[PDB]
Image (cartoon, rainbow, N blue to C red):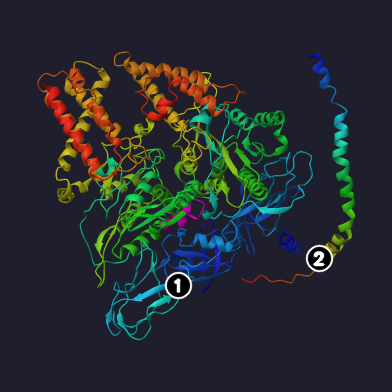
């Protein structure tokens, strides 16, 4: 249709003479042909979202509808690329522009047509019945992700009436003649899909095979499993990005996606150009890790709707990859910024919130957006098994109970890592409050540990109980200081102190403090358990703690330096050292005790 | 200190000569360039004044 | 070059302007017209009161033959019969040049110092266009200031947003003046400062500081006091940022910017948010000023193409000694780092009365350490922060419990604190401390402790300088 602009209000426009449209549908508007999606319609006046800047626009300007909702392009060339929130090639736009600005109305394609690829037909013979989700051939995209699978987009059935031969090809080429009713089934190497609607799947499954971060507190204490999610506060002194980097370089992820909404620009440019400096620490040294990474970085300065749609775009890409039966991870800049954008948009629309500045549906929208993650078995004959994991970097408003978004998250998630402000005040990073965080998966994940460390759970549980008791007795001692107190009191105090300075402290940048394996954590835990238990049973019959520690001397220090055990040094050399440490500790306790 | 105060008054005639040096050359060259492009720009502006620009806003 | 000669040709086609005379309504800072053809959203228009006086404004809302126009230069004496409205048909164009050095500019950006027009090399849009995200470089060459606290605990690398969270009735402006005049880059500079919603004495003070500094020739100001119409206060920062961009990213010069007041900016935005109804956000504020703040802070940093860089230092006033208040909270969301001051220290006669605990520079790791400084700096800062917090909480605890649960280290940390505030924080208004002697004093204070408490120091560094 050819509409006329009736009224303009900043990031809002009212057209006239609009008839027969869908309230979620792309539109080309104005002489510059900007991009906008209708939102609210009535009669012939359309309330249209504008995803760009408005300046000098006048009434009566032509308005061009599209007839389809917002979608993204899927296929090859996605990986190791950077786009805006609305899927626009930052690098291509920059190089074409040959400037340092972004023109208005540019339409650089999402996936370039300037690169050919070496396709290979699958095993589907012409004349066979086909359906969505069935691989019919693969192409090579990159070494780490070689054999990019090619699938029939859902809602697509028929009989293969032809197959394209192998060889080098680019996009835009029909490669599969199929017929549902007529030859019309023509498909090139890529395709598209609306962002709002998640793609289907055969079914879902349980969770197991815990994720790994390299940092002791998270994996050891509050387990994290792929096919799941959690909220991680960002303090900028608690390793804002160190956790993300460790995840990228250690998490056994087939693909990595990080998005940027509240990007201050400094962090944006840095992370962007320090990814090149990063290297793949997996299956040999591959200098580029970006082969597993694709980024959607968007600063606040872009239109709000872009920051709104960023997460939908990212999660859609995640689902597209996992459909190939892979493991994916998501990183979010700051969900609080996304919520702020949501409330801004709602207010601009002109409907009252109900949560001191947030529309009620926010909870439902967050729940729906979250619910795309998990583990599932793919759809189609090839029978893939995908898994989507994510993490939301919650950025508080300087408070905890002030922002309902916290409640919304805590009401839906199943693993949540809090934050102790005082730890940051002491620069005690990693700064995490133990008493608040929690992880429900520990229950199920016994069925996994029992295969590797069948004694880990109870040991961890007793350690956590000891930590809780120390926390409790602190509130009593502080008000009265030292008094008539049993040797067990000092035992608890010192063991808690050692645990926290060992566990809850570690340099974010060191070969022995920025990364740990499971077995090494197991050894640390067992050593501390043995230390405390032997000390307590010794003091059980006399053995004043002063002379006890003197007799054992520096056993606490003897184990303290164990952190300096460099991992990756054989796993038997380190394990042998830990066995020697346990032997000396047990014998020393047995002897000095008497 | 009295000597320094006196010398603070010694810089009263250098200022005028420095100003004259700073100005005179730029003044002269501005006056000179006021003639080369003079007629050229005169013609350009005069001719550009009379141009018609028939147009209609269509929307 | 020649392509530059081949682009100005557009400045030779002239088209008259429509002059409407159909004023339909006036409500304070807003005027409503009727029977308007082709509104052309975001237009600059001029008005003539029925006395010869001329003022101007911009349109904000448009529909069928109805346009809503704000105006800056007051609203008195407006009649609905004898006023004329003309349409320039364009958004705001700011003349630009190199000669503006040593020029005083009103809130509207005009020579208020007896100087003629700027003889512009071009007219620019106050609203530029976004920088491509894939076009920025990360700040480095940590610039110093001679201020122990700033230079040591919250050092700043040029190219970063750095709010100065000031409180009412504090010498924040003097702190900024000392910073700029004593600006030191050891691993010159153009300074443009905008004065908006400010009193008078500060203006003369800053002019005096620049004249005595002698750097007045390498700076220009945009002045906008309270008697000036409040509405235009939403414009001055745009002018400042446009000028800074022009100078930096076209002359490749390192430039620093100072903004006196964001509070007045938020006040003006709220002011013109109610003459027209708007679903208010927290404390009456329309929720979308987050966007405008991002727009203001969009301009900063460095890019590969241009050597010149820009650094922002907006002075912000806490309304009631508060951070969760919408202004400071929103600024913290998107800004970088922060500089904090407290009334207690000032009451204690301590200059500068900085409050370290809240003040944190989000970005310090990149532009520190070896190559330009000594790697000890990080551990020094961490240990100082930790011991300071420990001493503060120990004093607080004693204030309610007395000397009945005070470990020896508690009172050690106390006395350490008293000496720390007394000596380290205190500085003369004319002495600059390089990072070197700063760290030397840091180690002097530190060496009161044993080699076991200071766990925030690496054994290597813990042993290098514990005794020299």
x then y, percent, for residue A530 = 16, 32
Looking at the image, residue A159 lies above or below residue C52: below
C261 vs C462, left or right, is right
Residue C14: say if magenta.
no
Circle 2 marks a residue in which chain? Answer: B
Residue drawn at point x = 17 percent, y = 45 percent: A453
A543 vs C396, left or right, is left
Residue A307: say if magenta.
yes
Q: Nearer the viewer, residue A31 or A465?
A: A465
x then y, percent, for residue A469 = 20, 30
Q: Are marks 2 and 1 in contact (CB under 8 Å)?
A: no
Outermost residue on the left side: it is A541
x then y, percent, for residue C206 = 67, 31
Where does the magenta region start and end? A298-310
Asked which quadrant contains residue C281, the reply is top left
C379 vs A55, left or right, is left
Could you say whether the residue bearing mark 1 is in a helix, strand or loop?
loop
Could you say whether the residue bearing mark 2 is in a helix, strand or loop?
helix
The tag on residue B48 is 2
Looking at the image, residue A74 lies above or below residue C423: below
Classify the position of the N terminus of chain C by image quarter: bottom right
Categorize mark 2 by other alpha carbons within 10 Å: few (<14), some (14-19), many (20+).
few
Q: Is residue C113 visible?
A: yes
Asked which quadrant contains residue A69, the reply is bottom left
Q: CA distance from mark 2 to mark 1?
A: 53 Å
Residue drawn at point x = 72 percent, y = 54 percent: C122
Circle 1 marks a residue in which chain? Answer: A
The residue wearing badge 1 is: A116
Q: Nearer the viewer, mark 2 or mark 1?
A: 1
């Amino acid at each position: 249709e050819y509409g006329a602009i009736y009224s303009v209000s900043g990031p809002v426009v009212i057209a006239e003479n609009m008839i027969g449209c869908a309230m979620y549908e792309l539109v080309k508007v104005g002489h510059d042909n900007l991009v906008g999606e209708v939102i609210r319609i009535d009669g012939d006046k359309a309330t249209i979202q504008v995803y760009e800047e408005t300046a000098g626009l006048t009434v009566g300007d032509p308005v061009l509808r599209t007839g389809k909702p917002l979608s993204v392009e899927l296929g090859p060339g996605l990986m190791e690329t950077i786009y805006d929130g609305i899927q626009r090639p930052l690098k291509a736009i920059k190089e074409e522009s040959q400037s340092i600005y972004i023109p208005r109305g540019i339409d650089t394609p999402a996936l370039d047509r300037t690169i050919k690829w070496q396709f290979t037909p699958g095993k589907f013979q012409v004349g066979d019945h086909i359906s969505g989700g069935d691989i019919y051939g693969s192409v090579f995209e990159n070494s780490l992700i070689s054999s990019h699978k090619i699938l029939l987009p859902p809602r697509s059935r028929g009989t293969i009436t032809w197959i394209a031969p192998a060889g080098e090809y680019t996009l835009d080429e029909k490669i599969l003649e199929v017929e549902f009713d007529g030859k019309k089934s023509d498909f090139t190497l890529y395709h598209t899909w609306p962002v709002r609607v998640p793609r289907p799947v055969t079914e879902k499954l349980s969770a197991d095979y815990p994720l790994l971060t390299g940092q002791r507190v998270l994996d050891a204490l509050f387990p994290c499993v792929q096919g799941g999610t959690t909220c991680i506060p960002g303090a900028f002194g608690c390793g804002k990005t160190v956790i993300s980097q460790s995840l990228s370089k250690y998490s056994n992820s087939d693909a990595i996606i990080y998005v940027g909404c509240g990007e201050r620009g400094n962090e944006m440019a840095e992370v962007l150009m320090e990814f090149p400096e990063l290297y793949t620490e997996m299956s040999g040294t591959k200098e580029p890790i970006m082969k597993r990474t694709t980024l959607v970085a968007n600063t606040s300065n872009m239109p709000v709707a872009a920051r709104e749609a960023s997460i939908y775009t990212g999660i859609t890409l995640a689902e597209y990859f996992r459909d190939q039966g892979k493991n994916v991870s998501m990183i979010a800049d700051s969900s609080s910024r996304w919520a702020e954008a949501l409330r801004e948009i709602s207010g601009r629309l002109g409907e009252m919130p109900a949560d001191q500045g947030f529309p009620a549906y926010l909870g439902a929208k967050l729940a729906s957006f979250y619910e795309r993650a998990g583990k599932a078995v793919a759809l189609g004959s090839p029978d893939r098994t995908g898994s989507v994991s994510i993490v939301a970097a919650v950025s508080p408003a300087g408070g905890d109970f002030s922002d309902p978004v916290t409640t919304a998250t805590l009401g839906i998630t199943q693993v949540f890592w809090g934050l102790d402000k005082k730890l940051a005040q002491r620069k005690h990073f990693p700064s995490i409050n133990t008493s608040v965080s929690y992880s429900k998966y520990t229950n199920v994940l016994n069925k996994f540990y029992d295969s590797n460390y069948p004694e880990f759970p109870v040991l961890r549980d007793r350690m956590k109980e000891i930590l809780s008791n120390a926390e409790e007795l602190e509130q009593v001692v502080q008000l009265v200081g030292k008094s008539a107190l049993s040797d067990s009191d000092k035992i608890t105090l010192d063991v808690a102190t050692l645990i926290k300075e060992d566990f809850l402290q570690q340099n974010g940048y060191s070969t022995y403090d920025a990364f740990c394996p499971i077995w090494k954590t197991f050894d640390m835990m067992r050593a501390f358990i043995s230390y405390h238990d032997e000390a307590q049973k010794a003091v059980a019959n006399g053995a004043n703690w002063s002379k006890l520690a003197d007799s054992t001397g520096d056993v606490k220090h003897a184990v303290s330096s164990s952190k300096f055990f460099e991992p990756s040094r054989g796993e038997k050399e380190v394990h042998g050292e830990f066995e020697k440490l346990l032997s000396t500790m047990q014998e020393r306790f047995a002897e000095s005790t008497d | 200190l009295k000597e320094f105060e006196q010398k603070n008054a010694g810089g009263v005639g250098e200022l005028e000569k420095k100003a004259e040096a700073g100005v005179q050359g730029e003044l002269a060259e501005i006056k000179k360039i006021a003639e080369k492009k003079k007629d050229d720009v005169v013609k350009i502006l005069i001719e550009t004044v009379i141009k018609p620009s028939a147009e209609v806003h269509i929307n | 070059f020649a392509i530059n000669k081949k682009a100005v040709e557009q400045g030779f086609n002239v088209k008259p302007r429509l002059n409407y005379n159909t004023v339909s309504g006036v409500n304070g800072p807003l005027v409503i017209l009727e029977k308007v053809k082709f509104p052309r959203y975001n237009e600059i228009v001029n008005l003539t009161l029925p006395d010869g006086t001329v003022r101007q404004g911009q349109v904000l809302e448009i529909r069928g033959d109805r346009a809503i126009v704000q105006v800056f230069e007051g609203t008195s004496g407006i009649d609905v019969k004898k006023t004329t409205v003309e349409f320039t048909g364009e958004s705001l164009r700011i003349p630009v040049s190199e000669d503006m050095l040593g020029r005083i500019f009103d809130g509207s950006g005009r020579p208020i110092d007896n100087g003629p027009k700027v003889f512009a090399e071009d007219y620019l849009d106050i609203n530029g266009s976004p920088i491509n995200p894939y076009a920025r470089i990360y700040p480095e060459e940590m610039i110093s200031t001679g201020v122990s606290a700033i230079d040591t605990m919250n050092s700043i690398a040029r190219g970063q947003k750095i709010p100065i969270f000031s409180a009412s009735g504090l010498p924040h402006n003097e702190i900024a003046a000392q910073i700029c005049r004593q600006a030191g880059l050891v691993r010159n500079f153009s300074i443009v400062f905008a004065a908006m919603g400010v009193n008078l004495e500060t203006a003369r003070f800053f002019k005096q500081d620049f004249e005595e500094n002698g750097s007045l020739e390498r700076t220009s100001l945009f002045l906008n006091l309270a008697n000036d119409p409040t509405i235009e206060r939403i414009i001055t920062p745009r002018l400042a940022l446009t000028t800074a961009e022009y100078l930096a990213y076209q002359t490749e010069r390192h430039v620093l910017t100072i903004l006196t007041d964001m509070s007045s900016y938020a006040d003006a935005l709220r002011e013109v948010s109610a003459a027209r109804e708007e679903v208010p956000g927290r404390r009456g504020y329309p929720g979308y000023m987050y966007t405008d703040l991002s727009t203001i802070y969009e301009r900063a940093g460095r890019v590969e193409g241009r050597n010149g860089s820009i650094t922002q230092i907006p002075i912000l006033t806490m309304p009631n000694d508060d951070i969760t208040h919408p202004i400071p909270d929103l600024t913290g969301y998107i800004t970088e780092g922060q500089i904090f001051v407290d009334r207690q220290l000032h009451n204690k006669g301590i200059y500068p009365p900085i409050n370290v605990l809240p003040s944190l520079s989000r970005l310090m790791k990149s532009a520190i350490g070896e190559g330009m400084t000594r790697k000890d700096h990080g551990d020094v800062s961490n240990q100082l922060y930790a011991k300071y917090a420990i001493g503060k909480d120990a004093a607080a605890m004693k204030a309610v419990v007395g000397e009945e649960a005070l470990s020896i280290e508690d009172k050690l940390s106390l006395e350490f604190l008293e000496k720390f505030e007394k000596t380290f924080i205190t500085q003369g208004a004319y002495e600059d401390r390089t990072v070197f002697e700063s760290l030397d004093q840091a180690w002097s204070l530190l060496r009161i402790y044993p080699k076991e408490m200071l766990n925030r120091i690496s054994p290597k560094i813990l042993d290098e300088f514990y005794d020299r």
